[PDB]
Amino acid sequence: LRKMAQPSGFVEKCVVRVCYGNTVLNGLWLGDIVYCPRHVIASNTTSAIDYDHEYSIMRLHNFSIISGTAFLGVVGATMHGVTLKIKVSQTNMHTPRHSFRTLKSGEGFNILACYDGCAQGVFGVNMRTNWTIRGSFINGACGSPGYNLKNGEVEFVYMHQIELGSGSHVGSSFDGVMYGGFEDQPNLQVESANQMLTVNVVAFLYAAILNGCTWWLKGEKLFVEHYNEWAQANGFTAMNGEDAFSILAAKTGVCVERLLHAIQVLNNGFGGKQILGYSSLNDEFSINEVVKQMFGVN
Amino acid sequence: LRKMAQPSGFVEKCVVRVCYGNTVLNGLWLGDIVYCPRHVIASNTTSAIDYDHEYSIMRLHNFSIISGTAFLGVVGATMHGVTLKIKVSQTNMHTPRHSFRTLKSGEGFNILACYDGCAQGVFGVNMRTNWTIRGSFINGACGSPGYNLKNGEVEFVYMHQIELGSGSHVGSSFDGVMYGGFEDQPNLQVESANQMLTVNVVAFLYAAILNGCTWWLKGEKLFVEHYNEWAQANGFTAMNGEDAFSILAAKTGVCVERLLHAIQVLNNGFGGKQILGYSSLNDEFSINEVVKQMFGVN
Ligand SMILES: *C(=O)[C@H](C[C@@H]1CCNC1=O)NC(=O)[C@H](CC1CCCCC1)NC(=O)c1cc2ccccc2[nH]1
Ligand SMILES: *C(=O)[C@H](C[C@@H]1CCNC1=O)NC(=O)[C@H](CC1CCCCC1)NC(=O)c1cc2ccccc2[nH]1
Image 1 (cartoon, each protein chain N blue to C red):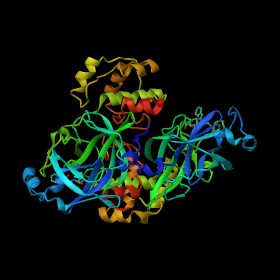
Image 2: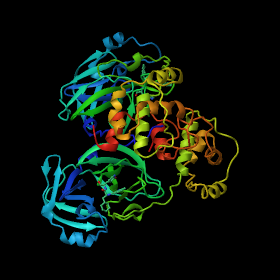
Image 3: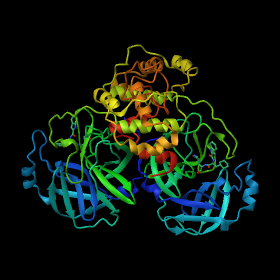
């Protein structure tokens, strides 16, 4: 069981460099629009930014947009939430089939980490319950896109915006809505406490059974409402959609509630043993990742 | 610290679907040659294989090679170690600048996991000291390529071949040499014992220091010679190349000998605490990765 990214080839062709005055970051070129964070036009980030004022003084000739080696001709730019839509005169002939989607709590996606208009890394990640992610971004990563591949099309779900004081990372949907409601402002912002994604830990243990790792499995069941009471006080999400696990419960013969029991126990530590090579419960893998990696089903 | 892959776009254009009879796996199409595992032509996989015999009875009309939706035309094939070089009429016009390199023990690289000639996932891995990797492959992944991006070119380093009884994964170089000397035969083969990569664990601990996670750091030094006598009997590799860590020692003020000392004690357990979110020592990240991810430098 390995955490994988979906391939990045369709997305790489859309990444561009967006320069405005004294700032450089990344943009996403789809059709004749380049999407990027609006804070690229902020002329002074020492203190609170009045983005209406910044937009009113914005001058189109201060933009430079580069795709690989070619300059794109900027013809207009409008502000939408915390993003800019920059109209260029060239159409990206490598625009993939795509849509835009806003992630829900816990949902998996892929980050293409880009610098200077060029992709440098790719990884799978989950939107955490506090609406941040643990990216690896350093300065210059803003505008890096997050995406999912689904039925032959690219769902664009994340545009990188800011790093919080804690080191956690916040982006926006491509509608311009910042995840978690955080502001593109210079001052300190603090995220809510993270919660372990219970549905993913369940999938993790099903994966463990399927690979023969069963030293932790016991016959006792913990009822869902009894588990949810425990979760609320111990930093775990509640259990929902138990039906979703039916394919895994059938193939293993282990009901969900026996794994809820194991979570409550295994949270106190593994005692030196390892589950699939991990020394603590892992919440990285969704049910769909587990069935895909072990069976080839989507 | 997040495990990442380098982007996959350049390599996706080279993956093809290779079918011989009723066996289907992946090929790597470079110039006018398709590289793939030679066991694609083995007519009976249930017993010892005489590849000289199988090569002598190979009939080229049994091949089907598809790139996306186009069929490639086979004009010849030759056998080189545990690979086949299949000469086609068509030159891959998306062949990147590239070379073939053979991994050293402990070296990091990227896998593009493919099925039916189509990339499905991408992840970073290390060649382990026992010449296996911890992959996540199911039937049909054979021929999936491993690569590194360096200096404006693709280094092709791994062609996926077999899964061992233990679940570990074994490949060959593209020059046809199986990593670890394993055979492309259907009998049980057992790998040697894996060792923890000391230089990676030292990189890991430096990353922890750089992130102000030093609860585990003490003042005592442990000399390299003494660490190494402990390592040889405790499942860790010897410490080498401590000059690369000089820049991190200088930057941090913490010499390598204080981290070797920490490895010795922390191997016994973390006492319920965590380091960068891990519950035990982690050997997945090289010094190169740590420096690239935190400081942007190759
Ligand atoms: C865009 O390229 C960068 C990417 C940041 C920088 C480091 N790691 C990242 O992910 N984003 C920024 O530089 C913003 C700048 C805008 C923020 C919104 C309003 C003004 C401009 N800066 C940060 O995100 C930032 C600064 C900072 C200082 C100390 C601790 C954390 C921190 N995060
Ligand atoms: C190629 O696509 C597959 C990839 C394997 C399949 C399962 N997970 C993988 O990574 N490789 C194979 O199918 C080889 C084919 C053999 C042909 C004859 C010579 C040796 C290779 N089979 C295996 O790798 C294999 C069979 C097997 C049976 C029981 C336990 C493990 C196991 N691994």
